Length: 122
Length: 106
Image (cartoon, rainbow over all chains, first blue to last red; front, top):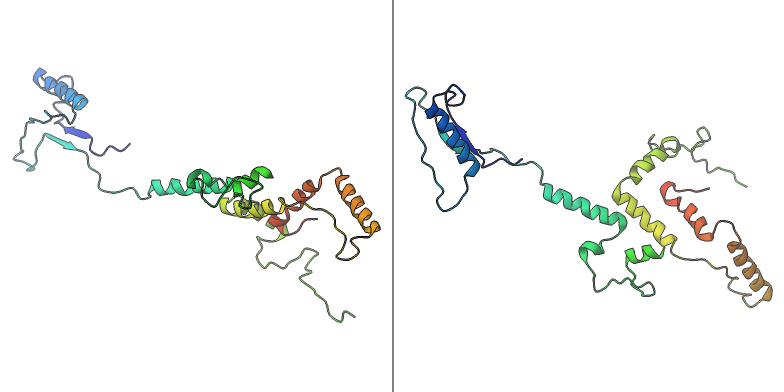
């Protein structure tokens, strides 16, 4: 659900409908294919109608990419990493993440038995 | 003679040493389960139990008189009877290891 950059097309309400003139309905159909087929290939581009309404001093048609004005509060990436280490800590299986060291060993008779290796002994 | 007394709390039979209501035996049990739920606490009190339940035990006569036949046969009888229990010595250590969660085990 990260819809930032999603293409948004704003049309006057007259265009959107069933009783609209065939020319208008054809325009809406083309916009549907434009939405459904637009990619970032070599021949990417747009020829859109542009009419700044003398009233309200704003354009009626726009093709714009939806934008967000904030950032997610919590960093999910570091959050999950903390719990993964905690889970491995509960089973004392840090060797899965850290890996085999040069001062740890799985040999029971060795003088440097790993914590996990001793657990299987119990 | 004991002219004084090591009177700890003696409130109503229950030991009222801990001034916090939560950590007293009627509710200390729950509190300990709740804290046992936590990962760090669980692993920290699990490693100690681990270490205790790792070593084995074998009866031994005192520093002197270790060559006496009576002491040797007594040690043998003690070890055999330790193995003669219907619950193994390791099982007894397991039952004791509630030691960490509460501080005492009857």
